[PDB]
Image (cartoon, rainbow over all chains, first blue to last red):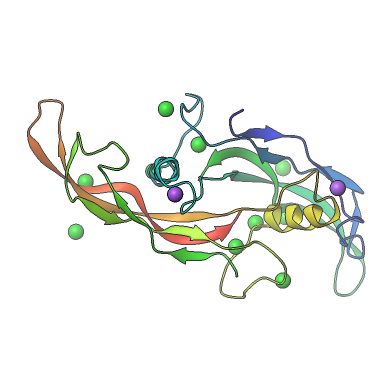
Length: 105
Length: 105
Ligand SMILES: [Cl-]
Ligand SMILES: [Cl-]
Ligand SMILES: [Cl-]
Ligand SMILES: [Cl-]
Ligand SMILES: [Cl-]
Ligand SMILES: [Cl-]
Ligand SMILES: [Cl-]
Ligand SMILES: [Cl-]
Ligand SMILES: [Cl-]
Ligand SMILES: [Cl-]
Ligand code: NA
Ligand code: NA
């Protein structure tokens, strides 16, 4: 239905990061999934440009794409990584790794 | 090619806003168009979650969508609008109406 946060468990080996991220093996990154269509749910905050673009898409669907459901706020995680020197070091707040909020943009 | 700002001229009559926005008739809203794929251009700032999701999409294309090219910063415009009382009033900075920057999210 509407744009919302859903589960996405990410494995660092599968994306080629295990050479440098020791632990954890996986983490919950989440993803934003769903449509950007009218009517909109009242528990989410849209931008005016996303509203305008969605309306323009309705009138000219071949020429203008619809707004996209994307992460609008991100949260950090902690990773145990391999530094340039190669020693296991803790990165306490590795920013931007997990979805906090979703929204149409 | 890559995610970038392109022209999108929006007509308020075409989107049903002319009942309340008197002037201007049209304005340059811009849109964000292009792909979110590796390698990425060095004149843009990606988020870690968008990078991770794009990598996961490559490994599992049917299960996880790619990051989306969206506006990451918006600019205001000035509109002459019809207030509840119905008198033409200037809104000097109507926020969020035009694309300032694009990015993969
Ligand atoms: Cl609505
Ligand atoms: Cl939204
Ligand atoms: Cl806005
Ligand atoms: Cl803490
Ligand atoms: Cl930290
Ligand atoms: Cl790259
Ligand atoms: Cl980007
Ligand atoms: Cl980030
Ligand atoms: Cl000014
Ligand atoms: Cl204002
Ligand atoms: Na069309
Ligand atoms: Na797949």
